[PDB]
Image (cartoon, rainbow, N blue to C red; front, top):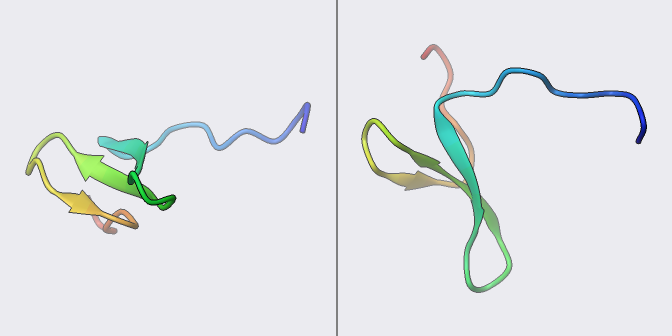
Length: 40
């Protein structure tokens, strides 16, 4: 807990659907995807 931080994250945003599922929203494409793509 105290230690162990991710650090830098993609340009995506962390959110959670109104059902109870965490997803990621891209500010570049303005899309919604559970996980974030690689090679960005």
